[PDB]
Image (cartoon, rainbow over all chains, first blue to last red; front, side, top):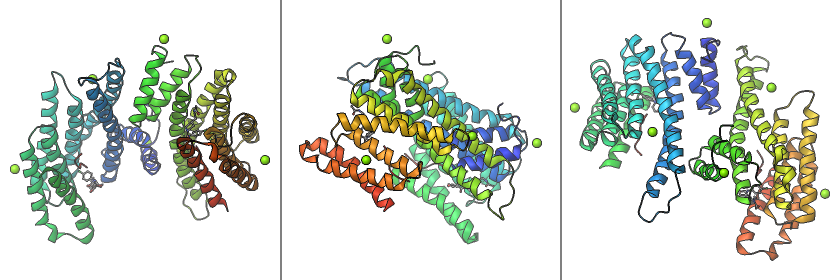
Length: 236
Length: 236
Length: 5
Length: 5
Ligand SMILES: *CC(=O)NCCC1CCN(C(=O)C2(Nc3ccc(Cl)cc3)CCOCC2)CC1
Ligand SMILES: *CC(=O)NCCC1CCN(C(=O)C2(Nc3ccc(Cl)cc3)CCOCC2)CC1
Ligand SMILES: [Mg+2]
Ligand SMILES: [Mg+2]
Ligand SMILES: [Mg+2]
Ligand SMILES: [Mg+2]
Ligand SMILES: [Mg+2]
Ligand SMILES: [Mg+2]
């Protein structure tokens, strides 16, 4: 790849610069290069990887939703026929989104997950696997849609099982996993009751463990707890 | 080019979709394809072209400024040596910026300007020529920097001469040209007094012609007049 | 749209 | 940074 000639440390340095410049496509490309060096990622480096791709795919998802809405409006009664362009451009954006998701899934499969033995790393990568299958599921309409949804579920569930055994209920990775899996249940799996139950139980179990935390850890955990509360408020 | 097989009208349709989705790189690529069809652009189409590239280069300029500031801080006394990475990445962004500017200048030279006979189109394109040479000047440090600055000046000046002869003082293109040429004087040409004089004279001449305008034209002209006032406030 | 991290 | 259009 195009980053093969760049030092690992330089790729990481440049990813941090790209983040400061809000150049998330560049950030993602630097981080992909760093992963492809073959060494395990540190905590900081896992965060860089995730931030980069979250921001790239986030932008693509927002664009896809704009275009999908326009396309849906075009298919209503009384809408004038404007030709294939809206579908074509929605497809273009969709294909680019799918490409990014496939790139991330590829990094996780070759070989981040299999080398991840500590709970913090393994849960984090399995959560990411769930997230990128979820993004594929958002745009899926064909023969494989059920298998894509099941791939997301399986990844999230493996992450949940490890997190419950190995991490305290306030751990930010455990909380973030639960937040996202709850959204999977609500938005993808047509399971709003499961979504609500998971968010409520996660919040309550975290609340009960806050007493163990330093001020700084408390700030980190409570930030994500508020996201759980925000979703619960949206859904109830 | 990659848009050679797409209908002109479809390119324009897709540029409008890309704008709605805030996909400005795509918007610019569609508009480049439309220009390369060889037909003159309408008013609406000239606006699409300009919006697309303004947004792409705007993002690149903001990133370049972040990276340049980091690089400058690295060259201060007492700063630890961190190697070539900041310079390299600033150069990467700079080269991409220069590429976009060269693409726009190329469209203007082949053959938008030479076919533009009406004042509205010719002034608009010459203003754009000035703007993209100005962006090149912002990053120039070599043998050609003076010639790049002079290219911007010459384009702006030709636009100003036509605008003063052919357009009323409230015309938004005339106002926008003056706004940008004033910024050229302040930021590029080291001529803050010229910048201030131009902004003041342009504002005052516009004010005196507002009485001729409809409500809708008044709204358009006064918006840009306020930008002139905003710059004057910054500079005095 | 719901919050995710 | 000053306003341009
Ligand atoms: C060692 C380690 O834990 N590294 C990676 C996990 C970090 C990521 C950043 N953290 C956060 O609390 C925020 N993002 C986030 C949380 C949890 C997950 Cl699984 C992913 C991302 C929370 C949301 O705002 C940004 C930071 C701490 C844990
Ligand atoms: C026929 C015609 O005049 N077409 C192009 C010029 C338009 C552009 C949009 N207009 C504006 O007033 C705004 N942008 C802008 C003004 C002037 C120039 Cl030269 C370039 C762009 C003003 C800033 O906010 C966005 C619209 C009207 C004239
Ligand atoms: Mg090495
Ligand atoms: Mg498709
Ligand atoms: Mg349960
Ligand atoms: Mg044709
Ligand atoms: Mg250079
Ligand atoms: Mg004068």
